[PDB]
Image 1 (cartoon, rainbow, N blue to C red):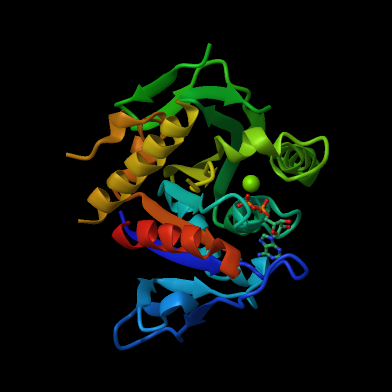
Image 2: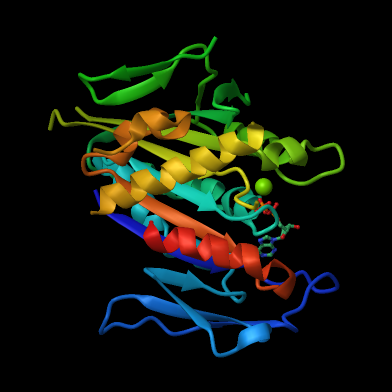
Length: 304
Ligand SMILES: Nc1ncnc2c1ncn2[C@@H]1O[C@H](COP(=O)(O)OP(=O)(O)O)[C@@H](O)[C@H]1O
Ligand SMILES: [Mg+2]
């Protein structure tokens, strides 16, 4: 049940931002300590350097393809029956959706592509895998099918489902295409896109991988790819408590975990416990105008 935290600094939006009054310096991974550190300083007091450590830090030069080089190995563990959770955390504008859904290389598209390649490869070993998914949103602690919804936890299989939620088989790149196209259009920022709403809700792309080796072996693993509501400072209190609860749970898992204190953590409890693997992605802007929210985000990531 390993937990890791990565930080990703997105490229500056030239013509809109600059780093005139702040500095974010990323150090090279430290193989003697096993982590990578970064320093953040505000011009108003350059003697105060805030240091942060992460399992890996991606800078403005790291593309989505670069990011996946470090995520591919995590997601493939689902074919072995491990559950996986990947959370994109950060203020609105930091790059959560781009990271998770950018057409072709986002974490979700890359994951599906990667899993498919592994499935085809595993066929030569007598393995037969079936893939199905759901795309939901949690807004104001209520579940919404983005494609009555009650959470059903099966203590027997240690699996979870949601009643009346659309689930689609993923047996073709064509089905993946239309679904990922709809997902992006729904969450990405487009004129006729509900970004306002999207920024205030959590979206979860769920992928179930069921395999059978007619060796007689069987395998079931679930991947939960979450694009969290913006972390920037009753709907607002819902977001605050939900993110805070998630932080409490992830941190507790890394040490009574408060899974039931939020809809999100309650939904994913089986994918957060046992030998499940969790990756927390903290997205931040490199710009001086966002420096305070950036420091907030980095502080949340630390305790996590
Ligand atoms: N890694 C990145 N590389 C290039 N552009 C990015 C990257 N991350 C975000 N962006 C751009 O920054 C803006 C913030 O995008 P978005 O992903 O929607 O943020 P958030 O989901 O956190 O609110 C978008 O216009 C997006 O295209
Ligand atoms: Mg977004």
